[PDB]
Image (cartoon, rainbow, N blue to C red):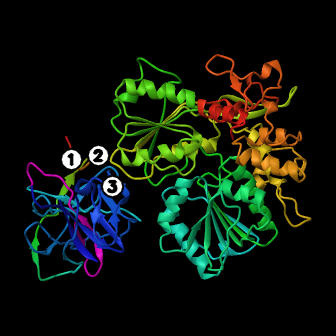
């Protein structure tokens, strides 16, 4: 501990800070956001205030006391090239409209700012290094100062705890490793569920030193008696529930980003809630936007400037100067990959560096957003799940595409939209910023209002299809999670299959890369997995179009037939990649 | 590079130090932009 100096054609200090209370405290003009090199990792700014010129590195602040009205405050004077020379003074008062705060008049040379000031006796009473020069008076500097691990019941069986954790509340860096630590101390079979693989990797980095075993979906089950915590994705857990009778009866399950509306994730939450009700496990759902929340503008640890204006849907030419004139990094949320490309090109025309993101390109394009410096990141809603960015602005038209099962006539899944996003979605898109403090408040530029009613979303029905197709000790039926239960009127178990149909239904999703609804429609018809004849025997209106032309596929045998599925799912030909995969499937290649 | 390995002292009070006088009433306009300034 103590008081250290912040140093930079040579080595020379620009300010001073306090290394106490486990935190390092300085001012903005001293650091302007940076890193401090010591054996105790690297210090990063967690909180800041330009209005009062303060920065707290790695947690805090802190500190934090206040001087008496008639107190002789003394100032430490650690200066470049000099020794610490204390100076006792009788402080004054700098009258302001927010209020009058004390101000000492001491002559100190540039680079010594941030030096501690002391109360009558004992602890620190504030920081010195900010003031104003008078034309009459020689000098003055304002006494600057600002105001201002988890429960054990979180492990109790038959209890689900929802932790509304805003980023960054030290969820991944401080909270989760603490929960895993306490779990290991209590000899608990702990399971950790990440939305995506990269998040799981971040967890691995954050859980170094702990017995953590990553679980791949290529493995149906894994076991060791070495008292270890399992770490896997939501979908991995779901598919393991669908493909193995050897699932561990975990007594503590923790799901990160538990707001995920992916069918696998919803089903997962259903099963977990079920196990909790069975009194054999304790659950922890971590999410900034729990299923019982409708706030598009939540509170962040860094100030967010909410701006509302007109946002381009397609390529623009003039009028939107504010988009390109912004000289920081920006995250733009698009409803679809098509719109994403259309925006990305128009952005690159202005000479901007644009990285595009989506579900099938996430694991390969997301690291690019960290290593290389860029100007724009165009993304679908996939970034609402634990995606961290070093940006200052979020552009969010608040529009998305929604899979809907049309039952009017033959059942078919369409992509209704672009449709206004859910309030939770908007909050999560807004949550990409307001993380790390900067002198310029993070800007959330948006358009339109969010819509609550998403009960016609196909993912709920698909989740119901996934849930009741999972074996479990009877008589217990795996139902949807509480808050999400009221979004479908599907009777429990009405999607249950038997034996080979179930196996086919799993293989269609896992090996065929087909959506849940499509896989269910094919499986419950009695069609074998390798049988692809159904991709061609559809109605004339089930013709799939690729770039305004009718698709034609050369079959496995060697015959050309038009791509015309018996059941039409819009998600298999939404983007060229999905259509490529589905064309690979229809050819009997995979 | 912003290393702060140089630590000179701690939070020690010392009433064997020098004293300098002041205590004026200064009209100050606090800006969210940055620091302080004089009125008019």
Q: In the depicted view, which residue is nearer to us: A469 or B32?
A: A469
Q: Earlier in the sequence, mark 2 or mark 1?
A: 2
Q: CA distance from mark 3 to mark 2?
A: 13 Å
> Residue B37 got which mark?
1
Q: Nearer the viewer, mark 1 or mark 3?
A: 1
Asked if labels 2 and 3 touch by Cβ distance under 8 angstroms, the answer is: no
Q: Residues within 10 Å of mark 2 (few under 14, many from 20)?
A: few
Residue position for label 2? B31
- Residue A233's spot in the image, x, y percent? 63, 57
Residue position for label 3? A99
Residues tagged by mark 1 and mark 3 found on one chain of the structure: no
- Residue A299's spot in the image, x, y percent? 52, 51
Asked if labels 1 and 2 touch by Cβ distance under 8 angstroms, the answer is: yes
Residue A464 appears in the picture as rendered = no
Label 3 marks a residue whose chain is A
Q: CA distance from mark 2 to mark 1?
A: 8 Å
| Chief secondary structure of the magenta portion | loop
Label total for image:
3
Span colored in magenta: A115-137
Quarter of the rendering occupied by the C terminus of chain A: top right
Q: In the depicted view, which residue is nearer to us: A14 or A231?
A: A231
Q: Quadrant of residue A323?
A: top left
- Magenta run includes residue A404: no
């Amino acid at each position: 501990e103590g008081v250290y100096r912040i140093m930079q054609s040579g080595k020379t200090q620009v300010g001073v800070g306090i290394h106490m209370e486990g935190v390092f405290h300085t001012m903005w003009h001293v650091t302007r956001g940076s890193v401090i090199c010591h054996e105790t990792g690297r210090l990063e700014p967690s909180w800041a205030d330009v209005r009062n010129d303060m920065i707290s590195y790695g947690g805090g602040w802190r500190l934090g006391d206040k001087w008496d009205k008639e107190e002789d405050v003394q100032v430490l004077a650690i200066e470049p090239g000099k020794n610490p020379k204390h100076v006792q003074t009788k402080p004054g008062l700098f009258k302001t409209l927010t209020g009058e705060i004390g101000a000492v008049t001491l002559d100190f040379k540039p680079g010594t700012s941030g030096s501690p000031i002391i109360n009558k006796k004992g602890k620190v009473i504030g920081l010195y290094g900010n003031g104003v020069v008078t034309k009459s008076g020689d000098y003055v500097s304002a006494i600057t100062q600002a105001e201002r691990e988890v429960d054990e019941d979180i492990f109790r069986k038959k209890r689900l705890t929802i932790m509304d954790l805003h980023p960054g509340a030290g969820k991944t860096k401080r909270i989760l490793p603490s929960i895993v630590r306490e779990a290991l101390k209590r000899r608990l079979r702990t399971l950790i569920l990440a939305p995506t693989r990269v998040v799981a990797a971040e967890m691995e980095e954050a859980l170094r030193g702990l017995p953590i075993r990553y679980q791949t979906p290529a493995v149906k089950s894994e076991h060791t008696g070495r008292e270890i915590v399992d770490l896997m994705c939501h979908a991995t857990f779901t598919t393991r529930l669908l493909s193995s009778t050897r699932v561990p009866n975990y007594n503590l399950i923790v799901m990160d980003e538990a707001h995920f509306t992916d069918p696998c994730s919803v089903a997962a939450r259903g099963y977990i809630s079920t196990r909790v009700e069975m009194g054999e496990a304790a659950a922890i759902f971590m999410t900034a936007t729990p299923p019982g929340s409708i706030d598009p503008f939540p509170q962040s640890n860094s100030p967010i400037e909410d701006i509302e204006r007109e946002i381009p849907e397609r390529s623009w030419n003039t009028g939107f100067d504010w988009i390109t004139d912004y000289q920081g990094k920006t995250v733009w949320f698009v409803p679809s990959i098509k719109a994403g490309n259309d925006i990305a090109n128009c952005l690159r025309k202005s000479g901007k560096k644009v990285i595009q993101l989506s579900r099938k390109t996430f694991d390969t394009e997301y690291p690019k957003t960290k290593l290389t410096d860029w100007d724009f990141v165009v993304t679908t809603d996939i970034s609402e799940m634990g995606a961290n960015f070093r940006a200052g602005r979020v552009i969010d038209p608040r529009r998305c595409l929604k899979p809907v099962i049309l039952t009017d006539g033959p059942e078919r899944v369409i992509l209704a939209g672009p449709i206004p996003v859910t309030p939770a979605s908007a909050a999560q898109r807004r949550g990409r910023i307001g993380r790390n403090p900067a002198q310029e408040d993070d800007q959330y530029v948006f358009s339109g209002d969010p819509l609550k009613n998403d009960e016609d979303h196909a993912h709920w029905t698909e989740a119901k299809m996934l849930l009741d197709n999972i074996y479990t000790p009877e008589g217990i039926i795996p139902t949807l999670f509480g808050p999400e239960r009221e979004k479908t009127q599907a009777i429990d178990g009405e999607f249950r299959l038997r034996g080979e149909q179930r196996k086919t239904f799993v293989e269609l999703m896992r090996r065929g890369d087909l959506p849940v609804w499509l896989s269910y429609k094919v499986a419950s018809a009695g069609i074998s997995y390798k049988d692809r004849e159904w991709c061609f025997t559809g109605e004339r209106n089930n013709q799939i179009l690729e770039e305004n032309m009718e698709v034609e596929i050369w079959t496995r045998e060697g015959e050309k037939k038009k791509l015309r599925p018996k059941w039409l799912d819009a998600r298999v030909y939404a983007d060229p990649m999905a259509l490529k995969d589905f064309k690979e499937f229809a050819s009997g290649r995979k | 590079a912003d290393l702060s390995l140089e630590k000179a002292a701690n939070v020690q009070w010392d009433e064997m130090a020098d004293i300098t006088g002041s205590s004026p009433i200064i009209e100050v306009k606090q800006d969210e932009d940055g620091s302080f300034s004089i009125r008019d």
